[PDB]
Image 1 (cartoon, rainbow, N blue to C red):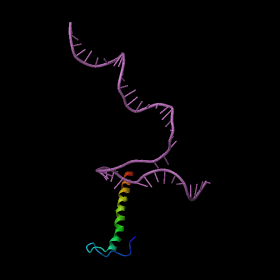
Image 2 (image 1 turned 180 degrees about the vertical axis):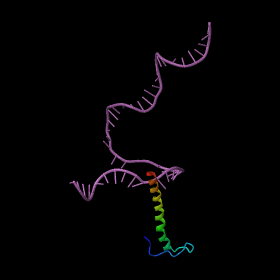
Image 3 (image 1 turned 90 degrees about the horizontal axis):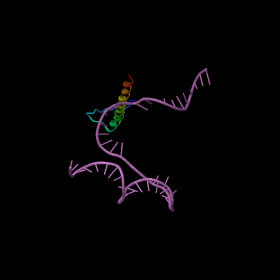
Image 4 (image 1 turned 60 degrees about the vertical axis):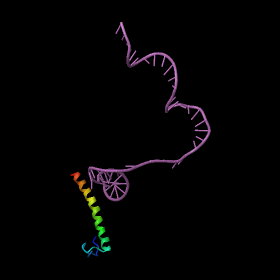
Amino acid sequence: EFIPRPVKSSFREGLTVLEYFINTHGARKGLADTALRTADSGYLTRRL
DNA sequence: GGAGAGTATAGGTCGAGGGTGTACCACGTCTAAGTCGCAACTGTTCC
């Protein structure tokens, strides 16, 4: 779910500590999500 | 009969370098190592 407080900083400005922490949630969860996605995709490929 | 629950199944590929032994005694029973003799067996040495 979206956090009601946006990150206003661009990476050119560099992010405050709180903004960086906030961004880590979606970054990491996206990494693990890709990890699972590439697995289930292969399973479906095997069944097909 | 018919519904919940309890049990069964599945869950990416290829690579590189690493990785383990608390605890009864007092004995007889057997074995794990032998040194050691004749046959049995390899070898020369001829005529």
